[PDB]
Length: 201
Ligand SMILES: Cc1cc2nc3c(=O)[nH]c(=O)nc-3n(C[C@H](O)[C@H](O)[C@H](O)COP(=O)(O)O)c2cc1C
Image (tube, rainbow, N blue to C red):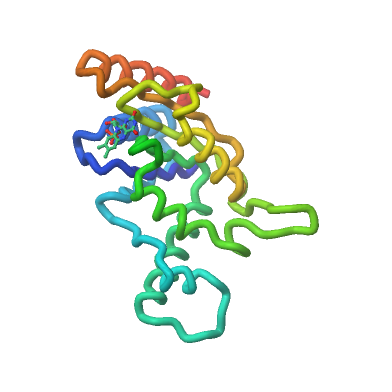
């Protein structure tokens, strides 16, 4: 029995291509794996704060008193990390905005990456502590970037996720959305088929 976490990060709400595919993933997983628990967190509808010079100190082990704002960010970081570690299958919807991930997803990563909690340093290098996960990235783009030099999102996601221990990552692409409704529909169909194959594994 698995627990599935779905992280939505688009700023386009119900018009989001990656959210539509995330919803399809959930629908198909419920159908094929009816006993599994599914948790969805919308990082745009419930925003994570920007990591600034005040919040960064909240995420360090210290005996120093924290500000109210720091205490709340620490509580949120702990909540996010507990949630991430409590689920088995992690689905990350990651649209490409100005050649980067969305800030909504980035703020989540910046509260989740914490030394001694989601990674630690050993005598022979970094070690990720978020273990036993299988990750699916659903990444939507207006243009066509896959396997080219302008896709920095894919290797960045592999790098960041691997650093915290999530090395088993399958990518689902929905590209060419900006070329119009016909190409957006083909991207949806192609990504749905990649999802079907993952759900059928
Ligand atoms: C603010 C913004 C920036 C974008 N930057 C890029 C980009 O750098 N490259 C690209 O191919 N598409 C870009 N797009 C198009 C989105 O990648 C495309 O609309 C995709 O469907 C977004 O996924 P979503 O619908 O789930 O938000 C951008 C869209 C927005 C709104």
